Image (cartoon, rainbow over all chains, first blue to last red; front, side, top):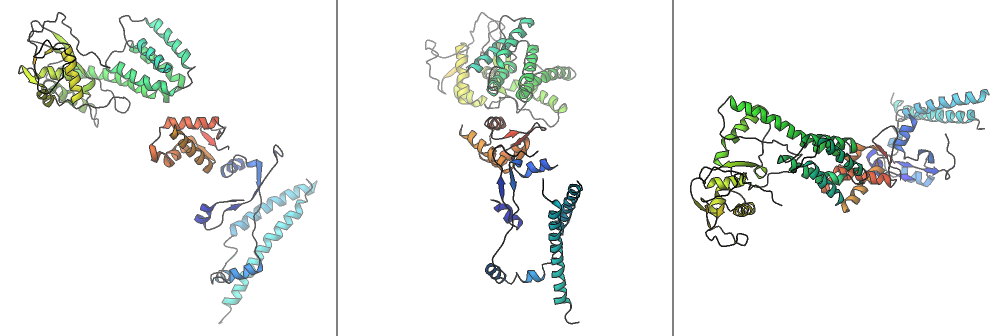
Length: 147
Length: 345
């Protein structure tokens, strides 16, 4: 795990990355290379980056949401589907690429790409519907009061 | 020391002697010098003592076969590169430019009131020559008018340029009208001023010469010593050995009226006479780790930003540090760009 305190402080969000490496002299698999060497080291193909996610317990969640008043105010006005719209469009784009690959594969190593594409589509649609549900709840809570 | 010796060989070769080698064999021995030159592992040091040797050769007009000088630097330029011979190219071009400048100045003199002495000057250039104004000097009353004249000629031709005359490296010729016969001696500007001080009176004390010429103590003492060596200034006690005579600002030195040297071309102007690298390497490796892919110019700028604020390192030292770090396989060149480094640990 590699952290970057300076960018974390200057950007307001944590900069973290988890990585794993390949065996010595094993797996040399085959605009991308230029940026890849620009932001990674010279050994771009020698290691890969895991997808980092965070979690918390129920007591931790309760204590955090009950710590300051700025955490339930920011939930009733979080306004999703606009904070991270660009991430949604990127997810739709690489979803389209994955669907094209699955269509190519199913016409004729053994991974069943269609199932993974469907899982990704269900995930992103579920985030979209969650955002819409938050907006609907906010509208029913605030707009539909006092005529 | 061997590079220095080879360069002194070069000096003889090009300088000047009683016998002038023919142009055919002059390049023949120069080719042999370049045969061993490439074998020399370190090239930077050779330019260091070649610059001052060449500067003394040209500023005194003691160089022989100036055409061979052009070909000599021409051979060097294709050997190591433009950057290695950039400073020496300035020295040769300054001599050629000033030689043309003298011809136009003479023509300008005829169309106006002529001078009283034959005046020639080498303009040189600032920033490329090792010389610098180091000794204060009072301009003699006889060498002032021509002085001003040339300044005018250098103000109408070139605007925005300021001249800084170097009296230490200036020579001249002085005629006499009071000796037994008509003599014509050669002396530097300092000796000329000292000998022209005696134009109106007979004897002066040392302090009376120091306050009239404003020359500093050491150079003035040396000039008086060499003048006494030429037995042109005679002390009161003739029998005292000149070398062991202790000079004080009270002796009344008088011009030797009875000078009777047989030669009429007396030449009294005879000449006289690690830790940082580790810091640069550390700065380079740190900058390379921070910026994974960099250009040579950007790397130089970053090194100057981070480290040059401390001791102002020289750019060739940083380039050599980059080369040795490349040899240590700390950072590698990238194909497709001549000047591009990637931090390969």
